[PDB]
Image: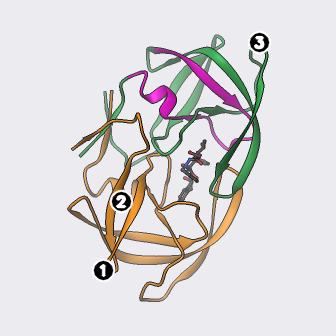
Chain colours: A green, B orange
Amino acid sequence: PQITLWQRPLVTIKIGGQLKEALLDTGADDTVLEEMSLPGRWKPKMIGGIGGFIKVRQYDQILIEICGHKAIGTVLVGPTPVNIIGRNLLTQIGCTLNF
Amino acid sequence: PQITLWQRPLVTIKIGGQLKEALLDTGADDTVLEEMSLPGRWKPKMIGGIGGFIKVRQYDQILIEICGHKAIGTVLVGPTPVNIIGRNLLTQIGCTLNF
Ligand SMILES: COC(=O)N[C@H](C(=O)NN(Cc1ccccc1)C[C@@](O)(Cc1ccccc1)C(=O)N[C@H]1c2ccccc2C[C@H]1O)C(C)C
């Protein structure tokens, strides 16, 4: 669909059988979700935001459904204020910015 | 124009007679720019992101040009790692997310 920006672009996502709300963020290189349990081994990663850096857990090849669209990619988990969908997954569902 | 997300969505902006590079961020409520001088009175404010909060100076009624389009709005100035155009200005140029 076409999403306007008068309010935060929040959509519902499905991961691990659970529904969660997440923000579509074109300014984020990666996707990071609030603390939760995911399968497999994880690797360490550092990501920087406006207030500094934070350590997160990187999980690969995770299935995640965004507004009915299925994507399979890298997902980070850590102390984030809100669940964030970044460019790595936005390109998989074919999302573009238009004006 | 239509902008793909394989790379960071950076564009050229004009403000205060100066040309700068900025990131179109749908995950940002406000617009924040690296330290610079702007006319008018300002108010202190605290904004939060990944990593924590930072203090910035808030300027109201500022004019900016984004890829030829003119927009008016509140602009925050502070120690941000990169110039960010947020929803408060993206709406004024008719920017939308599509997939
Ligand atoms: C390369 O690193 C990266 O891509 N990091 C990414 C990142 O920090 N992304 N954004 C852009 C960014 C920031 C710093 C450096 C580069 C790029 C910022 C963000 O949208 C995320 C965010 C954070 C908390 C809540 C909601 C959204 C944000 O900070 N939003 C806040 C903001 C920004 C400006 C003015 C006001 C406000 C309030 C709030 O909306 C992470 C991997 C997610």
- Say whether residue A3 is magenta: no
Q: Residue at x 39, y 36 (%)?
A: B5
Residue B42 shown left or right of residue B94 in the figure: right
Hey, which quadrant is residue B88 in on the image?
A: bottom left
- The image shows residue B40, relative to residue A35, as above or below, that is below
Q: Disc 3 on helix, strand or loop? A: loop
- Residue A82 drawn at (x, y percent): 63, 40
Tell me which numbered mark, 1 or 2, is placed earlier along the sequence.
1
- Say whether residue A90 is magenta: yes
The boundaries of the magenta stretch are: A70-93
Q: Nearer the viewer, mark 3 or mark 2?
A: 3
- Residue B9 drawn at (x, y percent): 39, 46
Residue on which disc 3 sits? A40
- Disc 1 from disc 3: Cα separation: 53 Å
Residue A84 shown left or right of residue B53 in the figure: left
Q: Disc 1 on helix, strand or loop? A: loop
- The image shows residue B97, relative to residue B58, as above or below, that is above
> Residue under mark 3: which chain is it in?
A
Q: Amino acid at mark 1?
A: Gly
Label drawn at residue B17: 1
Residue on which disc 2 sits? B89
